[PDB]
Amino acid sequence: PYNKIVSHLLVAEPEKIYAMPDPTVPDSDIKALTTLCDLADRELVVIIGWAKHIPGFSTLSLADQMSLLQSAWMEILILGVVYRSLSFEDELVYADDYIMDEDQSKLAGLLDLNNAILQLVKKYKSMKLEKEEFVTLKAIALANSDSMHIEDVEAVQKLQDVLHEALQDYEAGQHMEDPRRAGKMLMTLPLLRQTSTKAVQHFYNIKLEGKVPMHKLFLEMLEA
Amino acid sequence: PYNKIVSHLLVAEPEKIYAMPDPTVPDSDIKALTTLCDLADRELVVIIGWAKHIPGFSTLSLADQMSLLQSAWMEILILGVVYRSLSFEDELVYADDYIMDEDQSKLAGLLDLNNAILQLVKKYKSMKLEKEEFVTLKAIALANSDSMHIEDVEAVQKLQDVLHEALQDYEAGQHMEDPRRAGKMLMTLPLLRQTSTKAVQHFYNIKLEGKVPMHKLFLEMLEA
Ligand SMILES: CN(C)CCOc1ccc(/C(=C(/CCCO)c2ccccc2)c2ccc(O)cc2)cc1
Ligand SMILES: CN(C)CCOc1ccc(/C(=C(/CCCO)c2ccccc2)c2ccc(O)cc2)cc1
């Protein structure tokens, strides 16, 4: 039987979300970016709800909740896309109704970025990443997000340790064939940070945030 | 059984390299970058030599050797500065004769970058990073560098496994008090990737490679 943290993360895992592109609009770069914005906004709503079910998270200060989300939001988005794309070949499943191939990535101006995201997909395919590992890694990505402005270092570090421990216990219980599997999972996190870093700077480069700063969006969602 | 890997990493460890900045040139933005360029080039020579001592490295093809180095070189340079800087406060020690504080970083346009490196120093200070840990994470950084051009994926995966095992063996025998210490060390690698990624982008933005691309320098250094 799974440890309570992993099983809790499984029940907290949000339902499928759809991109729902406008069928009346001819495919273009603008259409793709519009659709991705629409998708991401819907996702961010449930990601904030999800974070508040990560044990420890809701009892941190508003400031610390905000810092972790500010630093990790794109990693969580991308990691979901990666998990969704595992049974596919050279394709990114943003949603069940929105799957982007190489050509479509080029048109959207996302080729180099999604190439790196396909690297992640490739690496998780060979490790045969399970859903339990995925939700836990997502939580760890949030907690291990390296914000510069943490107020309660001990609480955040305890949260990291709690989630690391949960991973390690799951691997000890479910993958005795590989005593080093948990560490292999943690070693995938640098490429996640890398691509997320490049995504976030592309995000600001082309001004997809709009007229309202992310900080202001998160504060709205967190105190709703 | 004995594990010789950490021991050979320790004997493979290069000697101190000195900046030797010109004592007749006015302390300025240009002087810093010149000092760092000339130090880094000498550092990279011993790094290539060091990498040749990593078991499995030089049995890779030249293309894969070059590919790991292309992806990792800045992480290796940075982790060295980080380790040299652990007994210092809010200062980065590029060499024994070249230490840079907050004000010198502004002069050189490196503040945002060095604040992130100091963030790494602060994290390692708290865990009490040991030399054995340091050298092994350097080796892991090389092997886990996520190059997109790898030919023999399996051999590179094996090298990662060998080094990961070494760290875990080391942690198990020497830090029984924390059964999760190896994983904590691995969770420091994202911030290093982030930091390097940003430094390499800056590297190219201000065009410090000069008239000879880094891959050409590596080919040259590897053939000597
Ligand atoms: C601020 N709000 C109004 C809009 C939210 O903005 C976003 C717009 C797009 C994205 C996304 C991407 C895809 C990145 C990998 O291909 C992006 C990032 C930067 C520039 C262009 C596109 C995105 C990523 C993952 C998703 O599951 C959904 C959307 C994430 C957020
Ligand atoms: C061909 N050759 C002249 C290339 C020179 O390459 C370098 C020049 C400088 C650097 C270095 C930095 C410091 C980064 C952290 O503070 C840098 C990077 C980008 C832009 C400006 C400075 C550097 C980093 C670590 C070192 O141990 C030595 C030098 C690294 C490489």
Image (cartoon, coloured by chain):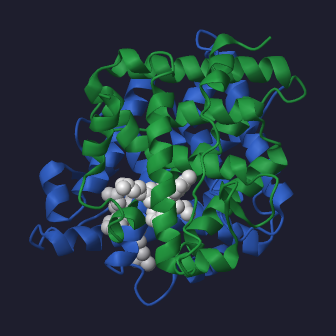
Chain colours: A green, B blue
The answer to whether residue B160 is left or right of residue A68 is right
Residue B33 location (% of width, % of height): 27, 71
Q: Quadrant of residue A95?
A: bottom right
Q: Quadrant of residue B222?
A: bottom right
The answer to whether residue B26 is left or right of residue B52 is left
Q: Residue furthest bottom?
A: B211
- Could one spot residue A103 in this view of the protein? yes
Residue at image position (58%, 59%) is: A20
Residue B44, above or below A136: below
Residue A222 location (% of width, % of height): 34, 30
Residue at image position (46%, 76%) is: A30
Q: Residue furthest front?
A: A24
Q: Which residue is nearer to you in this view: A8 or B45?
A: A8
Residue B79, above or below A178: below
Q: Quadrant of residue A45?
A: top left
What is the total number of numbered labels drawn onto the structure image?
0
Q: Residue furthest right?
A: A177
Residue A106 location (% of width, % of height): 59, 80
The answer to whether residue B162 is left or right of residue B75 is right
- Could one spot residue B43 in this view of the protein? no
